[PDB]
Image (spheres, coloured by chain):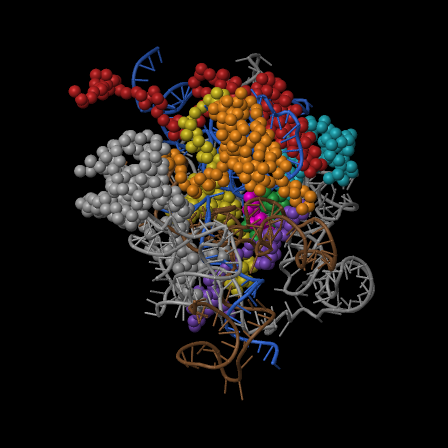
Chain colours: A yellow, B orange, C green, D purple, E red, F cyan, H blue, J brown
RNA sequence: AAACUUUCAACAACGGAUCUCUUGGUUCUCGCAUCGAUGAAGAACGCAGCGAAAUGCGAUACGUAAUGUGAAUUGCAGAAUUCCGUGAAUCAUCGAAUCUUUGAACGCACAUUGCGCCCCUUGGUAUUCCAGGGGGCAUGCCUGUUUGAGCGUCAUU
RNA sequence: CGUGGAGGUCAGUGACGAAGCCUAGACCGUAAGGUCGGGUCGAACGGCCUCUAGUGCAGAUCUUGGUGGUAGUAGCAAAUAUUCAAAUGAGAACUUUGAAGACUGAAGUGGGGAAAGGUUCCACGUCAACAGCAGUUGGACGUGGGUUAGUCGAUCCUAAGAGAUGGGGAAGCUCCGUUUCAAAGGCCUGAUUUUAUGCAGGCCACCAUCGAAAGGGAAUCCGGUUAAGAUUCCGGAACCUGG
RNA sequence: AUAUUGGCGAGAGACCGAUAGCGAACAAGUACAGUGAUGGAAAGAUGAAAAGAACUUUGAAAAGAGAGUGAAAAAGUACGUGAAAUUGUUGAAAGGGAAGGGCAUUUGAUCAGACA
């Protein structure tokens, strides 16, 4: 009566998709996300969860802008354009 | 021997920088030596292979056969000379890959830039 | 759910377009290690979890 | 087309030996389940009929 | 093939915008033919021709605004330098070169001399 | 879709997702110079917006469909 | 690595009959779940006694004893029955130690220096090398140590004037100053008597 | 006696050990200092002539521009002028651009592709109504400006 | 004695077959083990003096992987039940049409929906796997097609309640609080002929926002049509809100 | 001058060599499980070159037998080497409620050495 027949009553979602992390960890009644700390201003992480940091450090995604920084440093942050030598 | 720090003598560095070499650096790797006919003519030992050159095979099963290069196939580090093929059993024909360190050039194809390369490296051309 | 929202429906359109086998000409390329589609979903077996 | 149709049937074969009912059956078999073996059954209420 | 960039740089502004619309009529008509043909590889070249015109129209307006604000303080933010965040918030070459008026009198009278110990 | 051209006097187009009924009613009138009675839209299951455009009774759907070319 | 094997949250199930006490990986559904972890005998576990960096790598040796062994390494080069016992095809040269004039130091090219090494009598000992290059025996091939070979004569000079660059290429040959005199060169593999060619200005400096 | 059970060999199976490989790791040393309100890291969806993914990219979408190298790309189809040249390509470099919807996230809101307002402008006989196109509207604090408040308070009629 | 590497030596062995693996074939050592012949094989590997360790397995209800005996065995026994002929097919107890026979019996095995699933709905091609027998059929496989709204819903309002700002705590991430010890905010006409808005000058004192696809709620019905959609499309006839 | 398991660029090792080494040599923080915080694998090797078996005949087809490519199909997309458990056929041998072992010989199979 607590096992397989009352698993059949389970059809109301606790969590929905979060906007910041896209994780399906957004608790509806608490209005907050368990995984990525939304809507608070800081991304939730802890040093007890070390594996949770490796899943979401920098470099894990696209790095749309940081992949072009050290190339700009190696030239020394130049402007203008080429001269056609 | 090695007397610098910027060069590497590591097996695992040198193979990975060969197999994942970009397309423009594969031009230099697929160089072919000139014949002693042309070596007296220009005074230069080796040149990167181009499409329209004429060549002679000197090592392998196809030794002694010659032709014009159809297309340089840098993705496989190989070059497909026409009239050097395996005819299949079903009538079709398949070109045979060759590596250009074993080829020998007897006729060059010259653009403006091929003249500018030979004048650069110490040539004599005419 | 027959009264769905757009955010859920946009993810159903992505799971439909990924629901296909692998094309035949990728078999023939040079240094192909790809043999089948290893990320294939089916509605029958594995629920996509929203 | 008949060459790549053959390369489908040369590489489907490993999934049919495991009787994959598609190419999308990747239900993973657990080695050992906890509720079968992790207990000491004594006098009183137990975990199954 | 398609258009060349350097040929567009000689044309006027009214002729660039007319060049753009004439490509977009072609790109609309090749997508009608795409369902009739099994393959139509030409639609790549007319598509990059749309990108080549839009770069030139953008470049000619961004060079026209720099002359509108040349010789003037506070030019807009996307025309300024990008360099990075914490280098923009820094002391300039003027301000870090500044020193108080007392130290200016010190460094003239007593600078680090040049000398040597042999004889 | 060709069955709806002849009886319905209706063209069928595919429309970018951001557009609405006022822009389909405006752009069809501009590009083909053919007035629009009503526009109906929906979102396909594959993720793009379809639009049913019914031209007025003056303008015929077959003769415009030859000028664009699909038939 | 210090954290190898411990990237797991395993825990013992307890004491059933049909299971051991080695702490099982929790969770379910992935096939990893329910396997042993954190043991040395488990698959994918850590090893016994993870080897740390602060093992004693270098050995301190007494300085007076280190000077002692370099002295006994030199005095075996004269004896010349030990030199044949190590290798070094020196059966044709008349006297050992060989002393060559100081003009050996001032040679600039490699082609001239080999002709100097042939005419003193080190011909076959040069040719003992270059007949003897082989491959390494095991897994030392793809650890940047692929080829192995024998050693050759050792040339001692007083003052560098181009002999160290001339003999830098030719295989087997190792040149050495008098002030240095490496023990790792005079007795390779703790065998006395490497065949040494001396120069004259180096030999009178040895007092 | 056959069958059957057991033992060993031969060849054939099941199974993936051994031996040999290696674009991966691991530790050690040296050189350098560079993320973000000029919208970062992260996320969502989209992009190819034929792609599901990895890698790349943002309606200019496996890339546009500038420069260097100077004939390819390749599984196929396609392009021959694009080959003594302002010029090939999934090349190399990178100093100019685009940068969807989000995110500290910033008009308010968000389980919604919800709901306002201001300016410039075009169409609908319209400053007011409806729609399209372009541009704006968060909070804390500092310096400056402008308009103010208080019998806090001074002079002056 | 044997194992993985290291320094040295045998100018050691090797595509004329190195290492491995099999071998009721041979030889040596009391033994650890060593050597040789044969078969298989396809690229590197040994002897000897020394150095170094992640150096020797039958067990730990050992770890991972693989295979047996039991065994062609237990079993596939709830829900009243199947039968004949033809077509299709290499093949039919199971597919398809027809002829019979039965059941659910309007608190159904019928016709629509809410949570929930996500293309399963429909057509075409087709049977290696899957439907614990079968298979030509399928909720399987391969390729395509399909969801149309001024009126149906969401959006809007408030319920129990969530929650910023002004503030007050807190070392701090953050806590209390909902009109509070706060200077909290915009309408309505004019009068105009710089025409745009001066001033006329009154009134208001309330003051975030989120919270129901079942409560509250502006307004649509009938007949046709699709392989698959309709209070949405077509034909016909109405009503509502902002202008 | 000092610190540094992170970011970027380098150079090396008496280290490990696919149950090892990071969890990951491979579309790995991926497939998959959980409401959730989080948990989290398996998976490298045809050949020098696809020259990936045209064609013939049996079969409804998968495939089989030939032919052919190749140095090698005792390398055929289940692909380098393919060990043991376990199994099939053939050949030998034994056998009344076990089997296996020790000393000693018979019979049967098999085999090296030496006699110039």
The vertical placement of G52 against B71, above or below, is below
Name the residue at 57% across, 34% down: B56
Q: Which residues are magenta?
A: C30-45
Across and down, in percent, residue E104 comes to: 25, 18
**Can residue C25 be seen?**
yes
Q: Residue at x 59, y 17 (%)?
A: E12
* Most common secondary structure along the magenta stretch: loop
Q: Nearer the viewer, residue E77 or B113?
A: B113
- Viewer-side residue, G121 vs D42: G121
Q: Is residue B59 magenta?
A: no
Rendered position, E83 above or below C35: above
Give the residue at x 61% y 21%.
E16
> What x and y, as percent, mark residue A39?
46, 42
- Position of the C terminus of chain E, as image quadrant, is top left
* Residue C37 magenta-highlighted: yes
Left-right relation of F47 to B5 = right
Left or right placement of residue G87 versus residue F37 in this view: left
The residue lying at 46 percent from left, 35 percent from top is A67
Residue F21 appears in the picture as rendered: no
Q: Position of residue C31 (x, y in %)?
A: 55, 44
Q: How many marks?
A: 0
Q: Residue furthest left?
A: E119
Q: Position of residue G75 (x, y in %)?
A: 21, 45
Q: Nearer the viewer, residue H151 or E101?
A: E101
Left/right of residue F10 with respect to residue G40 in the rendered view: right
Instruction: Tell me where residue F63 sits by quadrant.
Output: top right
Q: Please state which of residues B92 and H50 is positioned toward the viewer in this rendering.
A: B92
């Amino acid at each position: 009566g607590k096992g397989t027949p009352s698993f059949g009553k389970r059809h109301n979602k606790s969590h929905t998709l979060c906007n910041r992390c896209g994780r399906r960890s957004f608790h509806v009644q608490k209005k907050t996300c368990s995984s990525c700390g939304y809507p608070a201003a800081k991304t939730r992480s802890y040093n007890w969860g070390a594996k949770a940091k490796r899943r979401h450090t920098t470099g894990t995604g696209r790095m749309r802008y940081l992949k072009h920084v050290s190339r700009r440093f190696k030239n020394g942050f130049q402007t203008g354009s080429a001269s056609k030598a | 021997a090695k007397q610098s720090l910027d060069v590497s003598s590591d097996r695992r560095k040198a193979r990975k920088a060969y197999f994942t070499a970009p397309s423009s650096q594969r031009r230099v790797l697929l160089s072919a030596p000139l014949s002693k006919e042309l070596r007296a003519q220009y005074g230069i030992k080796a040149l990167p292979i181009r499409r329209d050159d004429e060549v002679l095979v000197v090592r392998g099963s196809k030794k002694g056969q010659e032709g014009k290069i159809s297309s340089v196939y840098r993705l496989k580090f190989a070059v497909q000379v026409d009239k050097v093929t395996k005819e299949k059993v079903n009538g079709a024909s398949v070109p045979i890959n060759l590596h250009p360190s074993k080829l020998v050039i007897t006729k060059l194809h010259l653009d403006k830039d091929r003249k500018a390369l030979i004048q650069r490296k110490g040539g004599k051309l005419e | 759910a027959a009264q769905k929202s757009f955010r859920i429906k946009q993810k159903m359109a992505k799971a439909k377009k990924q629901n296909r086998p692998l094309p035949q000409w990728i078999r023939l390329r040079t240094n192909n290690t790809i043999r089948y589609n290893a990320k294939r979903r089916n509605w029958r077996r594995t629920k996509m979890n929203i | 087309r008949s060459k790549a149709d053959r390369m489908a049937k040369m590489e489907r074969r490993e999934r049919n030996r495991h009787a994959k009912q598609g190419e999308s059956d990747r239900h993973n078999a657990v080695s050992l389940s906890k509720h079968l073996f992790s207990g000491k059954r004594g006098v009183g209420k137990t975990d199954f009929r | 093939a398609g258009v060349k960039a350097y040929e567009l740089r000689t044309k006027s502004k009214e002729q660039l915008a007319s060049q753009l619309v004439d490509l977009k009529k072609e790109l609309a008509e090749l997508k009608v033919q795409k369902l009739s043909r099994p393959s139509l590889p030409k639609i790549k070249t007319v598509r990059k021709s749309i990108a080549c015109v839009l770069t030139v129209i953008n470049e000619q307006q961004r060079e026209a605004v720099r002359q509108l604000y040349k010789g003037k303080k506070y030019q807009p933010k996307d025309l300024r330098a990008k360099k990075t965040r914490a280098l923009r918030r820094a002391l300039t070459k003027f301000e870090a070169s500044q020193v108080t008026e007392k130290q200016r009198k010190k460094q003239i009278a007593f600078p680090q001399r040049k000398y040597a110990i042999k004889a | 879709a060709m069955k709806k051209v002849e009886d319905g006097n209706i063209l069928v187009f595919q429309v970018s997702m951001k557009a609405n009924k006022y822009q389909i009613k405006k752009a069809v009138k501009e590009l083909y110079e053919v007035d629009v009675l009503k526009v109906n839209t929906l979102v396909r299951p594959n993720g793009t917006k379809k639009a049913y455009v019914r031209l007025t009774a003056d303008y015929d759907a077959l003769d415009i469909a030859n000028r664009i070319g699909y038939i | 690595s210090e954290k190898a094997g411990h990237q797991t949250s395993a825990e013992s199930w307890g004491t059933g009959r049909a299971v051991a006490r080695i702490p099982r990986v929790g969770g379910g559904g992935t096939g990893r779940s329910g396997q042993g972890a954190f043991g040395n005998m488990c698959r994918g576990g850590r090893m016994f006694a993870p080897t740390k960096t602060w093992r004693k790598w270098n050995v301190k040796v007494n300085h007076n004893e280190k000077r002692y062994a370099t002295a006994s390494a030199i005095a075996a080069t004269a004896v010349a029955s030990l030199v044949l016992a190590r290798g070094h095809r020196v059966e044709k040269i008349p006297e050992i130690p060989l002393v060559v004039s100081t003009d050996l130091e001032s040679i600039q090219k490699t082609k001239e220096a080999v002709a100097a090494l042939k005419a003193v009598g080190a011909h076959s000992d040069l040719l003992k090398v270059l007949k003897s290059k082989k491959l390494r025996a095991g897994k030392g091939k793809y650890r940047n140590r692929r080829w192995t070979q024998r050693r050759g004569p050792l040339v001692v000079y007083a003052e560098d004037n181009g002999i160290v660059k001339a003999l830098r290429n030719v295989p087997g040959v190792e040149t050495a100053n008098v002030a240095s005199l490496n023990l790792l060169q005079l007795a390779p593999g703790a065998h006395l008597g490497r065949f040494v060619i001396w120069t004259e200005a180096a030999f009178t400096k040895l007092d």
